[PDB]
Every structure is written in C-alpha cells, then in structure tokens.
Image (cartoon, rainbow over all chains, first blue to last red; front, top):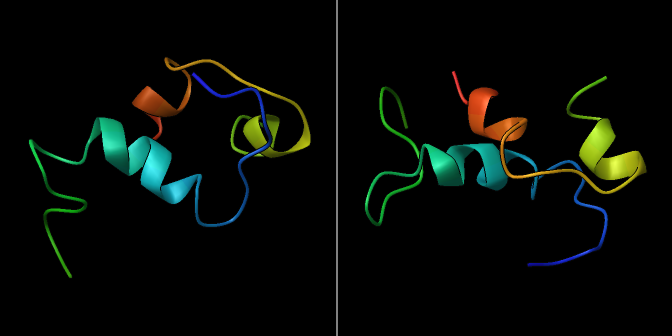
Amino acid sequence: FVNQHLCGSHLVEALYLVCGERGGFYTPKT
Amino acid sequence: GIVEQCCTSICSLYQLENYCN
C-alpha cells in the first residue's frame, strides 16, 4: 500500500483500477 | 469531498472502489 496523496489522474486510475477489468482501464467508451 | 479526500489527505481502498461509475 502507499501513504501518499493521489490527485487529478491517479484518482481516475484508482477508481477505474478497481473497475479496470482484469488488465483493462476503462470499458463503455474510449 | 470523497475524491478530494484521497488528494487532500490519504484514503482507503473502498471509497473510490465505489466512485467508478
């Protein structure tokens, strides 16, 4: 785990990581 | 906020796990 601040970008690929399939990033659109 | 949370301070692995819709 990391104990830093995640902002505008990391945040997107943090939430979209949980929702970043099994080696994906996004789904519906591109 | 809940997105600003993780940027202003440190957060968990559950909060944003529900903010990806």
